Amino acid sequence: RVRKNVLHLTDTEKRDFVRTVLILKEKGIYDRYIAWHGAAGKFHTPPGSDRNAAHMSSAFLPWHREYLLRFERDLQSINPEVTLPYWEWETDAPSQSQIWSADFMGGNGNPIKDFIVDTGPFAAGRWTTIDEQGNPSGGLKRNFGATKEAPTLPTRDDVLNALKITQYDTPPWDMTSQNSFRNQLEGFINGPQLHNRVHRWVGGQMGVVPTAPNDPVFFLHHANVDRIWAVWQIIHRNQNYQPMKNGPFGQNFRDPMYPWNTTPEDVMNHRKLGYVYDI
Amino acid sequence: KYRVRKNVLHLTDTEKRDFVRTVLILKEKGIYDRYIAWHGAAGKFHTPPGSDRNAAHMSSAFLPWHREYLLRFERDLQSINPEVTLPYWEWETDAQMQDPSQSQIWSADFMGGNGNPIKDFIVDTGPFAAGRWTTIDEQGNPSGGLKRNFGATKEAPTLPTRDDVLNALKITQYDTPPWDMTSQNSFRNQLEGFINGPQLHNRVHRWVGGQMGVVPTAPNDPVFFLHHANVDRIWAVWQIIHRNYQPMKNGPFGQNFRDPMYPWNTTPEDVMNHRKLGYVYDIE
Ligand SMILES: [Cu+2]
Ligand SMILES: [Cu+2]
Ligand SMILES: [Cu+2]
Image (tube, rainbow over all chains, first blue to last red; front, side, top):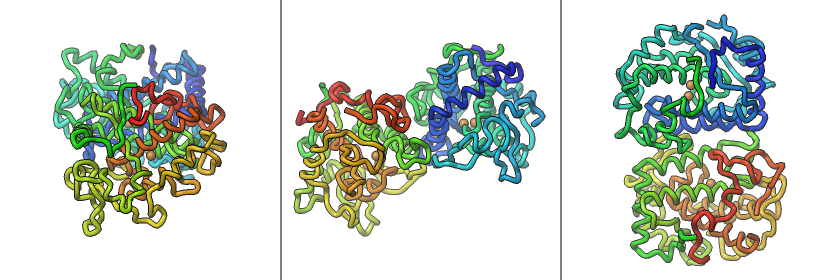
């Protein structure tokens, strides 16, 4: 509407973006998203399972799609010419990026302050955070490249190879699904790849599911994911969401995605939700 | 005004059978879990963050949040069987009993009885005995059996009485600044029951004990709904005499008349009139 390459934004656009987020934060609306996100990771389908309402199963993409939309709509309610932009990490793949500049996301974590980010719009003291329980946490943390599993960001080819996969998702609709676009993008096939890998590479809150959205980068990242998925939906036009049925409740096409009543089907056609990327 | 909520002791065996069945259905379908989860997610959402007030307790939204919660539940009951409604457990009358555990709410055909001391107070009678009914912990993780321990703690040796109810109905204000546990002369704070507590709502939870004894795991017990119905009923009666809400403004965001009550967009205002949500209580 359009969701643009974060690398293509003007210095006004970058600034207005940050501005808005921080307003969403002042009003108390931003915490709803953090918590909602936390709620869903705790909602396992069925209880005891690996899968939750937002990750490690089919609902992953529609959930985060519905997550971003609500979010964008809220930015719109503050400043209508703002759209959720996206961080094309595949061509970033790693900190020599403009995204981490002082004016935008801020930089990596301070190893001397326990990796609390001490620069950028959301450094500690300028930006409060909440832990997995929903109590004050002490600040945004980040640790680029720290773990052996995710020393680098996914490359272009990784992205192109995922887009070749013929089916949206396959039984048993979890992190072991094979030839599954969903599982490849999320990044569980020879993980961490793609989505899981970006998460492990950033570190800090972004490094753990129920705290990830404390980092505004979450939205630039999840926007890039959503984009890859929309692209895949443009490729495989003969293919649709799965499962349609006989998935765990919350994962099927016409199930409500906890914490909402929104279902995958409601979000299956992103243009319908009223926005596009840089084609 | 068409849905009617009846006093539990007034349900025939057949209505009790049906309500139990509808519940087990919400359970197997995986719908009932959304309720336990939402309830837990709310308690961990502080307004403001760090505050002792959460989106559903320890503050003004307590009654509205719980009525909205019941209304969504009943509606899910309704999508299975549109003749079923939320009953209420009039605990202040069972109080009167020499021994409330013998209250017919606890019979094997409805809620089930008291925990078994030898089996660590896991309930082993009724529709929701250990094995027939599963539970989750406050973290969204697998738990064990349903447990009950009627009137165990010294804090709540007894079920709140008629006079307790009657006396809370005398309260003139809905709630008072600073909109919390310390709010004085507040119907909301009174009914919730922590202040000058345990009484009423809090006391009931403590009286039952087991999962009901702790807030974030309480919806694991079906009676959670029967008791909060009685709570809705009582606030309904209050509202019959008093017929609305504070804080209207100014309060912590999520507590005011027109604020959304996490995890939803529903406001306290949306639920101020119960009749006009589609239900009345038998005694209406
Ligand atoms: Cu996520
Ligand atoms: Cu993520
Ligand atoms: Cu409660």
